[PDB]
Structures are given as structure tokens and as C-alpha cells.
Image (cartoon, rainbow, N blue to C red):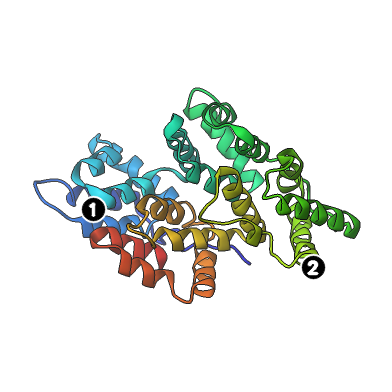
Amino acid sequence: QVLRGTVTDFPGFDERADAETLRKAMKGLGTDEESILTLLTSRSNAQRQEISAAFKTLFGRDLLDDLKSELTGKFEKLIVALMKPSRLYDAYELKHALKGAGTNEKVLTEIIASRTPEELRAIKQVYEEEYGSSLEDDVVGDTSGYYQRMLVVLLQANRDPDAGIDEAQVEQDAQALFQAGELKWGTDEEKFITIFGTRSVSHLRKVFDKYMTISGFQIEETIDRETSGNLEQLLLAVVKSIRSIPAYLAETLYYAMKGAGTDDHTLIRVMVSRSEIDLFNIRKEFRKNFATSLYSMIKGDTSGDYKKALLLLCG
């Protein structure tokens, strides 16, 4: 439960040597995707900006625009995602997800339910400086129903602080979620949105335990994962994130590689955003709840330079 990633700062880092290497890998009608992914995955996101700054000082060109020119396919999407500054990454995926009626609710649910309060505050600020409107206004405008209000509650980042576990508030909270669960989460939705949204993590931990001592079900067992709307998919993600954020994103990666096709966008988004936060913890929860290494599944579900960089980011 000590959070650590798989990509740290490259020791003995030279911004100008790395910038010259990337230019050599691209100048002249030729290819060198190996030299690109070898250097990019081995450098921290902060170092990847220092190289991008030295690349412009040395040659007066935009490193990202040149990489976009020389690469294509899923390998291009992974490289440009590795290039986006970590401070701007989450706000960039949300802005690209709020696309009107074609909004990707999976991206909104994944980021908003799995990010800490201190991370959400930085996203909201960054969103307003890079883009015109605010994140909350863009969410309200492109979503509706109690799924909208559930996101707006979480976007406030005003969850109760972890305090002394009131054993008397636990039984009442667990009894309230039971009645709403027995009505398929369709009766007075405002009541449990406040509980899932504002109660502290340690409290809702013990509330979820008292759920299994009251009913025979776990909280997740009363919500189907496949036949599920936006709200119930958000309850599932908030519950799993309250239990363990590394374990939730681990199951997010697992189902991105099972289906008629591999969700390469979710695969890229989850591994890039968490590469320096908790990817090492995500890998261990993967080996636990799925009886296989994340390295094993990526190798068997991806091809080419796109796969080689993913494996290097994994470990």
C-alpha cells in the first residue's frame, strides 16, 4: 500500500543529448521507432519536457509535431500520450471525452472516481486555464440525470475527512444503502449519492463491511457490471476506488484486453497516467485478482512497436 510507479527519473540525464538522439531518429527519410521508445519510456514525464525544451532550443522545431509526423497508428497515440505533461494529462482526456451526445462516460467515470481530492482540485484549475469554460460546467452541459449530479458531487473534492470511525453512523449508513440496493438503486437516488459522495474513505470502508453483515451480498454484487447504466457504473467505480484505487484501475486494464478488440485508448490512458503514481501497485493487484501478470496479457494482445513500449512501461 506504498504507492510507487514504474517510470522514475533517468539518472545522469542530459536534455541536449537525448534531444539530439530523437532528431537523428527522425531526420532523413527513414525510421527509428526503437530509439524513440527506448528513450521516451526510460525518462520521467518531467525529463520528457526538458528534452522537448532542448529540442526546440537546438533546432527550432516542435518535438511533438515532428513525432506526430513520423509515426502512425497505436504507437503514435502512445507516444503523444507519453509526451503530454502529467499536470495537463487528466484535464486533456476529460476535455476530449466531453464530446456532446458522443460523450465517453467511461473516461469521465474512470478519472473522476479514481482521482484523489487533491488531484481533482488541480484538474479543475488546469482545465479552466487551458480551456475556456470550467470542468463542472462542461460536465453539467454534456451529462444529465443523477449521473450528472453524482459527478458534480465528486468534482467538488469536498469529501469528509477520515476521523474516528463512528460505529453508530456505520450501521445506519450500511442500512440505508441496503434499502436502496434492494430497489435496484432507483429509489430516492439523491439519498445514497450523498453517502457515496461525501462520506470519508475510512468510513465507507467500514460501511461496506457492515453491508456484508446485514445482507448476504457485497455492494458490488447488487449492481451488474455488464447491463448497467451510467449511474450504476459510477457507483461501481466509486466503491472499487474506495476499496483500492490500484485494484480498480487493475481491473480496468484487465477488461480493456478482453473482447472483440483491445481498448487501446483505455490501455494507453491508464498506464500513462499512473506510470509514476501507482503502476507498480496496479501490477500486483493484477497478478492477484486475475492469476496472470499484466506483462503477460499485454504481450498477447498487442503487436509491434506499440507493444514494445507498453512492456517497457510495465516492467
Q: Position of residue 223 (x, y in %)?
A: 62, 56
Residue at label 1?
Answer: 21
Residue occupying the far left of the picture: 29
Residue at label 2?
Answer: 213
Question: Which secondary structure lies at badge 2?
Answer: helix
Within the image, what quadrant is residue 121 found in?
top right
Q: Residues within 10 Å of mark 2 (few under 14, many from 20)?
A: few
**Mark 2 belongs to which amino acid?**
Thr
Drawn side of residue 207 relative to residue 239, left or right: right
Q: Residues within 10 Å of mark 1 (few under 14, many from 20)?
A: some
Q: Position of residue 293 (x, y in %)?
A: 43, 73
Q: Position of residue 89 (x, y in %)?
A: 46, 42
Drawn side of residue 270 relative to residue 205, left or right: left
- Image position of 22 with respect to 282: above or below: above
Residue occupying the far right of the picture: 168
- Image position of 134 with respect to 185: above or below: above
